[PDB]
Image: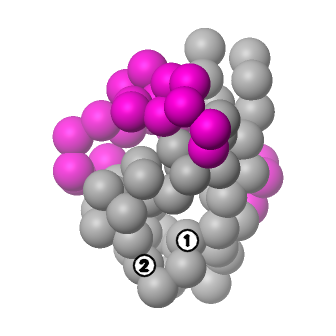
């Protein structure tokens, strides 16, 4: 349910994206290790798709770059 909004600066190698997610989410010292590893991502604030292996993210980065879109949303459920 919880929605998160993030924009992929300098094309993250996923780890950068995860770390950025945690940087935003509870920067203090809560679940700032891994976002439940159930990260789900949305693009152009319109479509929702979920990743885990460094492959779906490859599709997303290419999508963002090719589409020109950069808005990304992250769902935890």
Q: Are marks 2 and 1 in contact (CB under 8 Å)?
A: yes
Task: Pick whichever, 70 or 20, lies toward us.
Answer: 20
Q: Residue at x 67, y 58 (%)?
A: 6
Q: Residue at x 56, y 52 (%)?
A: 23
Q: Is residue 14 visible?
A: yes
Residue 33 position, x and y percent, is 39, 33
The quarter holding residue 58 reads bottom left
Q: Secondary structure at mark 1?
A: loop
Disc ID at residue 8: 1
Q: Secondary structure at mark 2?
A: loop
Q: Residue furthest front?
A: 28
Q: Is residue 55 magenta?
A: yes
Q: Is residue 62 magenta?
A: no
Residue 2 position, x and y percent, is 74, 23
Q: Residue at x 39, y 31 (%)?
A: 34
Q: CA distance from mark 2 to mark 1?
A: 6 Å
Q: Residue at x 50, y 24 (%)?
A: 31
**Label 2 neighbour load within 10 Å: few <14, some 14-19, many 20+:** some
Specify the principal SS of the magenta part: loop
State the quadrant of the C terminus: top right
Task: Pick whichever, 34 or 5, lies toward us.
Answer: 34
- For the record, the magenta segment spans 27-56
For residue 57, above or below residue 26: below
State the quadrant of the N terminus: top right
Task: Pick whichever, 30 or 17, lies toward us.
Answer: 30
- Report which residue position mark 2 lands on: 11
Task: Pick whichever, 10 or 55, lies toward us.
Answer: 10
Q: Is residue 67 visible?
A: no
């Amino acid at each position: 349910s919880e929605i998160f909004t993030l924009l992929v600066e300098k094309v993250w190698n996923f780890d950068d994206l995860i770390m950025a997610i945690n940087s935003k989410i509870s920067n203090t010292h809560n679940n700032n290790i891994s976002p439940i590893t159930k990260i789900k991502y949305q693009d152009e604030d319109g479509d929702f798709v979920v990743l885990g292996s460094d492959e779906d993210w490859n599709v997303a980065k290419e999508m963002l770059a090719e589409n020109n879109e950069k808005f990304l949303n992250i769902r935890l459920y």
